[PDB]
Amino acid sequence: LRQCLPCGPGGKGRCFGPSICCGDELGCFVGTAEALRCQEENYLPSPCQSGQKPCGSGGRCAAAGICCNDESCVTEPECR
Amino acid sequence: LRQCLPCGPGGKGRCFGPSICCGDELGCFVGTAEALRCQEENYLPSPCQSGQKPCGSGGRCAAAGICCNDESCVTEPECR
């Protein structure tokens, strides 16, 4: 599968959704200027590979201590 | 009730959780440096007033198109 789109400061983050941009050390940007690029995800039916640990309801440990699916993010200790 | 703590760039955002900082036009920062100040919320038992529309369950429209509670945020059109 294709890698998820790079986003945020220095492209250190990855798009987990159309409006979600996260990096392990950066945290998660939801609906901010940093996640603007991620809008392209809506035009790629191809699911992407982040390589992050699965979590919650079909989620992914998008960042340290944060579990996000394509539309939400929750603080999760298990993601540390 | 006390107003919620200010956070983010130019203090235009406010803390909805210990790790969540949002601004109507800025979007939401979950676990990012912008939300570091929000940790202080953990040492304030009393609830704060954000003056924002309710949403989901316990959630508040923290930003245009985003509903958040103390530990999570979700893209929500009802918040636009």
Image (spheres, coloured by chain):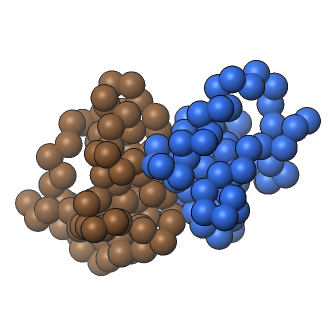
Chain colours: A brown, B blue
- Find residue A38 and report its horizontal and vertical position in percent: 35, 70
Q: Is residue B74 left or right of residue A40?
A: right
Snapshot quadrant of residue A77: top left
Snapshot quadrant of residue A43: bottom left
Vertical position of residue B47 compared to residue A8: above or below: above
Q: Quadrant of the C terminus of chain A?
A: top left
Q: Tell me if I can see residue A60 in this picture.
A: yes
- Find residue A68 and report its horizontal and vertical position in percent: 38, 45
Snapshot quadrant of residue A37: bottom left
Vertical position of residue A21 compared to residue B49: above or below: below
- Find residue B30 and report its horizontal and vertical position in percent: 49, 47
- Find residue B54 and report its horizontal and vertical position in percent: 77, 48
Q: Nearer the viewer, residue B46 or B34?
A: B34
Q: Quadrant of the N terminus of chain A?
A: bottom left
Q: Residue at x 76, y 21 (%)?
A: B45
Q: Nearer the viewer, residue B45 or A79?
A: B45
Vertical position of residue A64 compared to residue B77: above or below: above
Q: Is residue A36 left or right of residue A78?
A: right
Q: Residue at x 35, y 66 (%)?
A: A8
Q: Residue at x 81, y 37 (%)?
A: B48
Q: Tell me if I can see residue B20 in this picture.
A: no
Q: Residue at x 51, y 64 (%)?
A: A31
Q: Residue furthest right?
A: B1
Q: Residue furthest left?
A: A1
Q: How many marks?
A: 0
